[PDB]
Amino acid sequence: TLPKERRYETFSYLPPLSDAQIARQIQYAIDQGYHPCVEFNETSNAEIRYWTMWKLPLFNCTNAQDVLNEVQQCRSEYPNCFIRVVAFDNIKQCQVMSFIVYKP
Amino acid sequence: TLPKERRYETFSYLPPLSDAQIARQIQYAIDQGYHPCVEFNETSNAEIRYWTMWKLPLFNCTNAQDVLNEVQQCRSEYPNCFIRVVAFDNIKQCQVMSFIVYKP
Amino acid sequence: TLPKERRYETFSYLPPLSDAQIARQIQYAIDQGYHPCVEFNETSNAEIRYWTMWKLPLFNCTNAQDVLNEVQQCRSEYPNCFIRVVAFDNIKQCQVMSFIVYKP
Amino acid sequence: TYYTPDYTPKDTDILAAFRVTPQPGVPFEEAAAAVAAESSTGWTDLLTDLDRYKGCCYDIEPLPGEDNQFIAYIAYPLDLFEEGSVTNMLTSIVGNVFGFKALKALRLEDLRIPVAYLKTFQGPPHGIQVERDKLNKYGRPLLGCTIKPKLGLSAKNYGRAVYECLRGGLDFTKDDENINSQPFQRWRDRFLFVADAIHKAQAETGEIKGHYLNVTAPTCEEMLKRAEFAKELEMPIIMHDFLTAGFTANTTLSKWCRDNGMLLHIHRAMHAVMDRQKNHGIHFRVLAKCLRMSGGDHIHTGTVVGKLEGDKAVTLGFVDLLRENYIEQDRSRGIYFTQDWASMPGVMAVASGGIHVWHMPALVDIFGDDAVLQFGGHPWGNAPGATANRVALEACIQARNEGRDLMREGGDIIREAARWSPELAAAC
Amino acid sequence: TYYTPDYTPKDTDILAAFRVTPQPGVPFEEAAAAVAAESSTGWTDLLTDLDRYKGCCYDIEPLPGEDNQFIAYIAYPLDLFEEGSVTNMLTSIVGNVFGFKALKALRLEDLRIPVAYLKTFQGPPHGIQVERDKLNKYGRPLLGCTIKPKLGLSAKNYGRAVYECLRGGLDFTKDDENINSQPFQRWRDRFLFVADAIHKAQAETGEIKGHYLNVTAPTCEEMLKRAEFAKELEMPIIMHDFLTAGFTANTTLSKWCRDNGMLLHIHRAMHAVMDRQKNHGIHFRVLAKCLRMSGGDHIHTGTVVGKLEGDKAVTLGFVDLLRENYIEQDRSRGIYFTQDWASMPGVMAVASGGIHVWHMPALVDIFGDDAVLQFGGHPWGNAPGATANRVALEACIQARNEGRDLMREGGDIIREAARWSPELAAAC
Amino acid sequence: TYYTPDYTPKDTDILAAFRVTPQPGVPFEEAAAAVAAESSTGWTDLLTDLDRYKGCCYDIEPLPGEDNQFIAYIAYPLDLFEEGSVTNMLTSIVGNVFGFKALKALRLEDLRIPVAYLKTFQGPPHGIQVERDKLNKYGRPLLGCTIKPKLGLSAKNYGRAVYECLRGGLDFTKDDENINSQPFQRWRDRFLFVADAIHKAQAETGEIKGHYLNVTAPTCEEMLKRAEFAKELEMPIIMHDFLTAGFTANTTLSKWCRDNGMLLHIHRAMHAVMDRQKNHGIHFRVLAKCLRMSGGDHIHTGTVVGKLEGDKAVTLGFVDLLRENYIEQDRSRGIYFTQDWASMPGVMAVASGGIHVWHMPALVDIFGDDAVLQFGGHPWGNAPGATANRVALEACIQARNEGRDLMREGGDIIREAARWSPELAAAC
Amino acid sequence: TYYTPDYTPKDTDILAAFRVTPQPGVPFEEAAAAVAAESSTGWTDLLTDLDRYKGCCYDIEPLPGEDNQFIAYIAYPLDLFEEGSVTNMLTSIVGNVFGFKALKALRLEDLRIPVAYLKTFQGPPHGIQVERDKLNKYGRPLLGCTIKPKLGLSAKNYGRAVYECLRGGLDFTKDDENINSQPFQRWRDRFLFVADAIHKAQAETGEIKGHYLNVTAPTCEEMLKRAEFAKELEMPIIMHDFLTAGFTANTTLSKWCRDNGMLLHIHRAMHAVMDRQKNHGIHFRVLAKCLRMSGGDHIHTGTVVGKLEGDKAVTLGFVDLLRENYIEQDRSRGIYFTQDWASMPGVMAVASGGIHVWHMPALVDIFGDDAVLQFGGHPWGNAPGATANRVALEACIQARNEGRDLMREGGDIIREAARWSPELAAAC
Ligand SMILES: [Cl-]
Ligand SMILES: [Cl-]
Ligand SMILES: [Cl-]
Ligand SMILES: [Cl-]
Ligand SMILES: [Cl-]
Ligand SMILES: [Cl-]
Ligand SMILES: [Cl-]
């Protein structure tokens, strides 16, 4: 019998990802030429459309660590808040990644 | 990253005013010939249109102090209520001031 | 004081044409590469959209005489019908002439 | 960045040709870049690919003789513009750039509308060829008179003047652009008495008659209500002041005219506010192209009488832009770009202002058949003055068709006709 | 006949002040008469009393210094004009006269709209006072950001930018005047994501937020459909390009806004095509009076930064004409006539173009409370840049109310605030 | 006359590539001419310029191996076709020519739609990018389940099945194409209990859910009524059978979906009647282009499982034609012409038919993110079956993003995930 | 389970006869079960009684001579199908099954529509008997001409051709199926000039005239708007392309025709894409029964000239299915089932393609009275060519009525008539 459990779109069906797992996902985005960004919010449900941006997108540092740093900086300051990583394609002007990295 | 925090219209982006600061604003209204009045409400949000009047408007006292007294009196009777001072221009039948003078 | 008199569109404000004037009109149409045609009808007024075709359009005789022959043969067989010469521009798919040549 | 002299424009680009006057000390290349930047793109920046939304100046053309002036050619991508919207095309191109501080003056001279953009517009509700077929009028220019005085006649006295003009042999009469609905003459009363005048003239002459009933109005609802009343009265044609009313209202009316089979006469009130000074504004040919796209069946194009041969060539240039399917680039006539209209119908050119019978041969020769010749006094009054103009025109057309030279034989042609027409004689 | 220097204007007359440049060898008196005649009346003649329909020049004012220029004052009878129609008022006055051949140039400088004509218009759908009451915002200028880049963001990305700006303390964000509906961003998707952004900012901050959603459109039907969907989303404000769309469409929208409680922000795209050159066109102050009559709640009035004290005085002159009930004649500020608005509501002045936090003290001092200060990058992004501007503003207002002199103490007032606001400090 | 191998096609021409099988003894050049003639023009003749209305064969390409078959390339002028009308485009090209007696068989393989004709169409009401923004779903394919049995469940039982599926982690469930409204289950009851199921799943999971509610109907009125009721219930998505309903109905519904913010899922019932035989009919890729132009947000593209590498390549060819902006000519994948879509939005590919969890890695690898994977029994039922497919999907996407090779490591990826997911394990 | 050779079909069942080609190695019994399963039902399974929703093959009929082909008879319960919906019936029966992999080919040859299902449909808006009563035409076939060229004539030139045809003695002229609304000819102009042509021909001849005005359109709204304008013009008949527009649009139009008294001519553009190959697709007689159900008053049935006696018998078979009340099973004419139409009105057969006067006796003999004979050049033009056909027709009908044998005496009958008709003579 399935349990009832709030979920969080992409990757929320997997066990939580390790900082090393997060950095691999970020590395994929950098290697595709996408622009990673960090965002967080106090809740998540179906009706919420926007989260809040953490600082700004980092536009092309070549290394996944500076982005990870941001995740963990956000995680330590805002530990009651959901956090996720987003990646933008600037060519097609579309979002191509949005994954839950931390849940309270 | 800007924090998420409730605001309160004019002067809610400054440090809460000192009593001497409230007096100087009230004196500006008196010197312009405006009619100051005090009001309070239990909550404040975008959706609330009217607050509750404290007593009556003060209809031409020459001195900021009697208004300030009213603010102090309200603040002590209702420490769980927001308070603001407002000023009316009777010529143009328009409100020309509305600033937050006390929060919980 | 201008009389009240029924007209018949292009050239109806001139003296009725001679057969020689009718021939020069036709020759122009031929020299411009237009396709002349003869048409007749029992009445004329503003509500009438279509006249009746006399035989067929003449499809690239460089002489205006057989066109004129058709008018003459129409005029004599149908002495009670108004008659006219039209001409078409096949490129533009539009009519470029339509002039009255005989009234009962 | 914004000046790219190696860019070759796509067939889908919108192109603009601006006559630029830079401020003293601004070099041409900076002014040209500025023109392209200020008429286009001007952290979220790196969420988009700004390259594909910029205009660019792809050519700077100096102007021999002119002081500190040049032609900037700008290309804009198709995707910047709302489909079907002359309003958005104008806002995007001329919305902003004319106020830029590094320019002393700016004038938009021409625009190349690409086929892929044109197919998003309806264009004229009818166009030249359909209009002749509805009115049954072939092989000659049409003829109109304006009513005088402009303002002041009661609706009924107004209709009397219209009846007398039309019964004389004119095809059309015309509301003044100032007459909408006013205390001395409410629109509904005018529409009604004008319809009576047309009905009488049409029945007496056996020719289709019309009157450009002005529906220019304060609001779109009010404009459409005047249009519907003309349609109720079975009027074949109405009129609109496209610039003072605006292209939003005009595009509304143009579609309604298509939907309802109504002919649409466009008056160009206010054009010289923008289109007159050589250093600044928008050339009338640009406003004319916009009108063809939004839609009208006729448009005033100015007179050619008493104008230099170079003004005349410029006029003929835009008249081709209004009437033809394909117009080749031709700077001797102020055509900056080749313009392909992809079968969008042409608009009738209306010639008016200070014309009389003795101009007739020249008018027919200059404009040919696809024009309205709008006149507006004969010694004997309205109906005789109309007969005079109608016999003159028919005489010119006969002569031309006969191979006579209207520029040399003009007065002769008129003099011959004056011999069997008393009205025409009285007009000389 | 057309020049009557002894005529004294009635309180019901419309008056026009034209700057006139006659052709070489045309005397002032004939040019004056021509301006009056060609902007009015220009056998049936003796059926009407032409006297009561003519404009007349009642005064000719030579211009010391200027070469071959003068001011012609024209008076027009109340009965010439359609009630409630800016369209007809423009067509009447400026429809024709700017192309007259005896004039080298012509500029309409000012109009005196009589009380009796004003009463036939609705005016702003709300006006300064009602607008503050709806928004609950008192005792200060309002604050807006434009979103950048102008074009190219997807609807959703666009809404993200709006949310960050608003949540930082701005009252409004703004669609660019070029954004209507395009392949990269369809209007309905934009309206929807912007409403989500407003709802989230307004709930986080506890302050009413808005965004001027641009309803400028190809036709009146599509404009009203965009307005209706903003209403359906409970948006408090929308925007319209009044000049590229036209006064017919704008008047329709202004009535719809009154009927539906919607605030109306007016953008002036294309104004410099007509209003920029000193010798020819129409002065913006005329277009502003027309907009006030047709209707708007806000209108762009240009910036005062980096402009001479004489340009500043002219801007301030027309700002008063937009906001006040009664404006006294005052040539040093370009006010040619005393203008009485007979209780028609005033329009908020919108100051924008090249403004930053250090301009704040000057902007507050120059415009006072009844203005929108429209900005549009902070080092830390949208929300911090918004807080920086919002603290700067509140600091200046506190300082003003305290008696401090914002022109001398400005930098100080800003430096003091920067001490306890890190966002504001980062902006210095 | 109809065979002109020197003609070079204009960018505004519509091009067609027909596989032609002539009758024994008909030479290729006559069959080609006949294909061009019978799909176009076929005394009044000399009233028109027939040249500009003919299609022409501009190239004949023999087919190595094939018996008596060749590819005829036809060009049609832009002016033949009604703007915005797929109906008229089909009628014109395929209305007639397939019954011509000199042809033994005829198959239309591809069409090159020119930019100038594409701009007259709306296209998908939303398209890939907008749809992800409305649903909030990024960086992965979407997932759907069809409900079983196809027919026979009461509305309420049907909703119970929907809720269990959705609450398990699927984004969408789907009406069978056969279910419209029937004695065992009326559409209004189904719409209402499906909306209850969605609301409960969406509130339990915090993810946006949808169900393609089938509005295919006997008339346009009844189709739009079913649409409006879905809108009234705030459903995000509906479904239409485009071929059995028709393009006229589909175009209507596609415009209504754009007007109302509704997503449109298109089912391709009946396509194998026409598209299956190699010698005769219309290739699906043509039906797919037509559908993109009329409009849909999703369309079934068939499965890739258990098909030859050459059938796979063909599917991938038309999947690109559905999703991309620019598709380069490429015969090895069945693309006969380069196709520029001019920013018309792409349509999501829907893969369905005989798919299970162990196909997951190949499906992600083949289609990438912009696809809906439509499944339709798990041992423990609907919700567990859904969780299995959802974990499997998320495992493959994580693995891919990590650089793992989904074709070689597939089983491993699944086996690893099965270790911490009991539902996925039970499915192996 | 799906093959039940003992099932006897109920009178309320829908029956289908499919010609099946199985893949090599698939036995007939499995292919047959697959056909029934894949066109029907294909834990929640045991919530429903799947028995009462399945199709079954109740009979397998081998085909002597044919290689690997047989007839499968499928029975479907009444409850599967939406009332009044040809769209849902087609979707149900042919939606899916044609792509099943175990079949090499599949063609639907016939359907038995049960009386209980037929009573849910309107059928023809008028039908044969009512149509003759409205047109006042008894005891003979009707006559039509198609206008040539197909495309390119202006609306006015088009109308001239229609007038000349009609006034010669034809009952109807016809729009081409390609003519909807196009740059060279907009629909509203065409409708208008065609109405004038009919009015003039009807007044000159004293016989009711009509022209099948094509209302095929991009959307249902636009189709209905064209239909309403024909109605406003008092046109007796209009035309629709039922397959390229679709059955949803057609059924909408058919109801509208019934509500408004308009006759509906149905053109079968595209039918050969599905209906031509013997091994795969859907036989025309099936599309024909569908059209009768959705509704039309005329349909194209193909010509009988230059066809084998067996093709002829097949055509006559489906012509009886279109016109009669009760049609007995008859495989020598391709009738697979007895079809009872339960008083649903018959549709007029339209014979066209390559017909000339000398075919007249055979046409009358083959079709009898209830047909439209559609021709489309006489040496003397349109009106004489029409007289020739009309005299020829009347000569044949007189001859038949007199007991003459039209197959043997045909040329004689024509020769006798040619003696007193110069137009008919000229045509020989
Ligand atoms: Cl010029
Ligand atoms: Cl003019
Ligand atoms: Cl100035
Ligand atoms: Cl501005
Ligand atoms: Cl294939
Ligand atoms: Cl499928
Ligand atoms: Cl046929």
Image: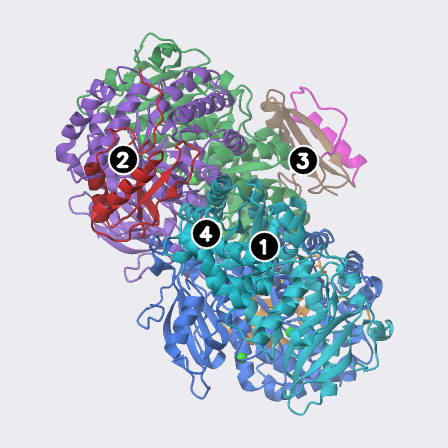
Chain colours: A orange, B brown, C red, D purple, E green, F blue, G cyan
- Image quarter where the C terminus of chain G lies is bottom left
Q: Which mark is residue G140?
A: 1
Asked if the residue at label 1 sits under 8 Å from ligand 7, the reply is no
Q: CA distance from mark 2 to mark 1?
A: 74 Å
Residue ID for mark 4: G387
Foreground of the two, F354 or B95: F354
Residue ID for mark 3: B19
Q: Circle 4 marks a residue in which chain? A: G
Q: Which mark is residue D277?
A: 2
Q: Classify A38 as above or below G144.
A: below
How crowded pointer 3 is (Cα within 10 Å; few <14, some 14-19, many 20+) is rated as some
Foreground of the two, F178 or B36: F178
Could you say whether the residue bearing mark 2 is in a helix, strand or loop? Answer: loop
**Where residue F112 appears, x then y in whole percent?**
44, 68
- Image quarter where the N terminus of chain G lies is bottom right
How crowded pointer 4 is (Cα within 10 Å; few <14, some 14-19, many 20+) is rated as many
Going by the picture, which residue comes out furthest to the top?
A: E6
How crowded pointer 1 is (Cα within 10 Å; few <14, some 14-19, many 20+) is rated as some
Asked whether the viewer can see residue G422, the reply is: yes
Give yes or no for residue F188 being in the magenta stretch: no
Q: Circle 3 marks a residue in which chain? A: B
